[PDB]
Length: 284
Length: 284
Ligand SMILES: O=c1ccn([C@@H]2O[C@H](COP(=O)(O)OP(=O)(O)O)[C@@H](O)[C@H]2O)c(=O)[nH]1
Ligand SMILES: O=c1ccn([C@@H]2O[C@H](COP(=O)(O)OP(=O)(O)O)[C@@H](O)[C@H]2O)c(=O)[nH]1
Ligand SMILES: [Mn+2]
Ligand SMILES: [Mn+2]
Image (cartoon, rainbow over all chains, first blue to last red; front, top):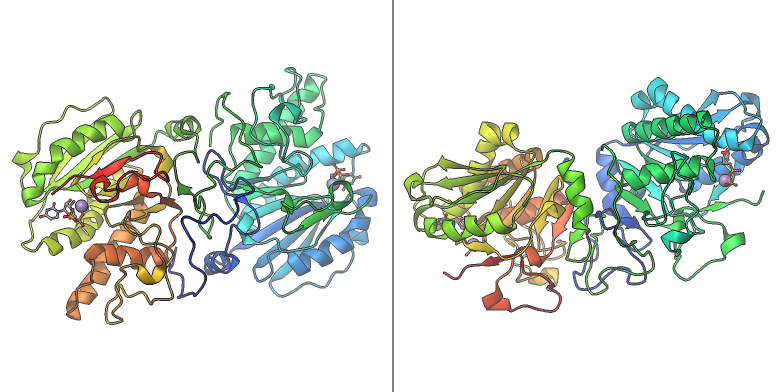
């Protein structure tokens, strides 16, 4: 990496934590990203100097096309502003994608794919489709991939602080829960099985990412695991999210995002521990 | 990575920090390594699965050969035990290197180099010498390089928790100090110059490291800066440490080690904030 320029900002204080109310590093030394833990000016410098391109995948199959306008418009206000962004919209209805005005250095591609009848299958098949397009396109077109649900909107900054070889996001329903309470797949017959004495966190299927290489590996593995389960007459309790959790248990993420990055205010309010609500559920 | 095996350990608690008394992550999201922040079993698994080899460089020029016996014997007890280790002892007196019994998977190489007259030159020229041998040997022989002073002994675990592309260590004299008090080079004529309003930390010249590529970059850059200074007729106030600090200001380390890793118990005692004293000064 090339040198940063002179910058003036508050000195970090070794004997003064940024946050004392939350865990800010995992036991494998991956940062857990909360507001107050990062200086976004330093991080922007680091990633801009490397001319980073970020891909964002989103699936808008069947009626879910209705979520695209707000998803994309709010993404324009909050997601990686100042950096190169390439949106990839996976849909069975190219003509139904709204014409959203994009900022400079940002582009959008529509990837036409099949629709599945069951929402579970639409959700699950994202793994296969992302993996497939890593090979077809993403490896050549972007440096990182961020893979999210479409039934969401950005309300605050989501930026290069999340970028790392592999990240998961704390599910907003479980961040304060004991591992026994996590809704991992519990049947040993399933490839997603995690027993009650294992597990670090419950990650949300709605927001993960990393380098293209790591996301390719993750999505390929989750898809293969789902195909094995299918052959064994089993479907994991929480579908792709169950498999995501099994993957990230055994392949530790190099950053973990706090629930600021995946929230539902209707269901969970605005707890003191959340200084910002960045990416939130839209009522559906 | 390849998958980790099933492991049983206590669950990380999102709403319960491991350490509330110290900063455990930098504003650029690099872990600051303190006892309690890492699970060494997880980390050992990760690095052993990668067949990691760690190089350790140490200079024992002139009278400093006296320190080698204790340095090496204690390294055998505490440094990277269980992993492949390659010691590189730089000396003007190959015959004076004590014969120290090494554990399996550990090797020692004696590198014969010139002895400079001025201690300042001895200390400063380590940068050139490390950089030269990165090309000569380290690139093909080790994955990471750890570069330390010889007038030291290991007293507790120093392991794979430190490994990362680039690391510096908090100097024990300044970890609680404001940047204005840091003994950076303050003369603008010097390549190591840092203004009073810049600076994250004061890093110790006695303990830094990283991937071979990053250590080659750092040591080459510091040597070049020193040569420019020499041509301009100036020598930085704290020699190689001043240049190391300039380098790490502009090239942020991906981990920072706490003063557990670089201490002087005679001068500073054993404060409560240090749960372990791992690598400590030998009186001289
Ligand atoms: O008919 C569907 C069902 C699902 N999805 C995609 O699959 C994601 C996950 O589904 P959903 O959001 O309904 O799951 P939930 O958040 O309720 O767990 C959605 O965001 C969409 O991106 C879709 O496009 N069309
Ligand atoms: O005559 C010398 C002077 C320096 N050194 C090496 O340079 C390092 C830095 O010097 P020193 O330890 O004296 O610096 P200090 O810790 O006192 O700042 C030493 O640990 C030795 O490894 C050496 O080998 N011989
Ligand atoms: Mn959703
Ligand atoms: Mn020393």
